[PDB]
Amino acid sequence: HYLNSDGSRFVPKDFYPKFSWDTTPMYYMFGDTTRLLEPEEVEFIAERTDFLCIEKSHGRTPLGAAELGAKHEAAAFKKIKPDMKVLFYFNSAYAWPFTSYNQAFTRNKIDEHPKLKSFLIVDPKTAELAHRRNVFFFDVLNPELREWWSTTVAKGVAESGCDGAFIDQMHGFAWLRADKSEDVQKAMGEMMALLKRKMGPDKILLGNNANQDIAKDAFPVMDASMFEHYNEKLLSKESLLQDWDDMLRIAQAGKMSIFRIGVESDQPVLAKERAEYYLACYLIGAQPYSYFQYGWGWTLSSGSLHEFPELRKALGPPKGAYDRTTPDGWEFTREFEHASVWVNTETGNAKITWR
Image: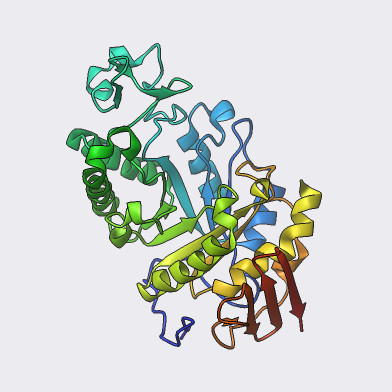
């Protein structure tokens, strides 16, 4: 039985990806608008992970629709690794026009789909559709959007043969309706609860940045949550310690966490250089069925196809929880079966002593 860092046992659900402390537990996420993966690339990634997600635009150009990119790679990976878990990606907030499901959410087609247009946040200072570079915003407060969006993701998961969904964005643009923020948080939870049911019984629900308080209504139905570390405030010593508390809490709920590092928030040289530091940041808080993601972005070219040697080194089960070297300091150590981790999250230095 895998052991959380408090000594409690972690009991996974039947449909969770495989987990092991043999080496660093890995999660990969990638996509390429311009091409599908070569077989060699599928083998490279399949050898290093049991758990991955295909990105928002993958294979859109060669195949016309991003969900066919997901469909193609899910089947390629499962031919190699039948037990592999592949998530379909869908944004809960931005109506990225990359899938066929979202093909109407463009400036020059949305008016021709009034029902879908009514699902979108209107900018009050324009009475016009709010947008970010003409990409429209789903309105989680709109119950029909919650029904349609959740059915749509479930449709994307089924059409792609993916093992679940990576849901991006939990905020429901609360800052655009700050008076309704609490309602937005509750609506997010309802939309996730719908999707979780509509997906059927053996499907993984991963929510991006779902450790955050704004996702507390979303969190319970989630199987997994990702720590995106999308900027440098999230890599502060305070945030890293909060990550570690969150990771324990997630594991005690029997859920999965993805500790993702993009070194763009600190390039292949810099990443391989910094890999010892950011791995150690993960290993301090690592829990059963938590996974490390590493690179410098979310494209196929963003790290998934590089060798960071530390990730492939023998790790072994933790010998215990981490130790805060001094009760108010920012040095942290943790012992694993085959490695000794040391990290100072104030100065940003680390040493993993592989044994």
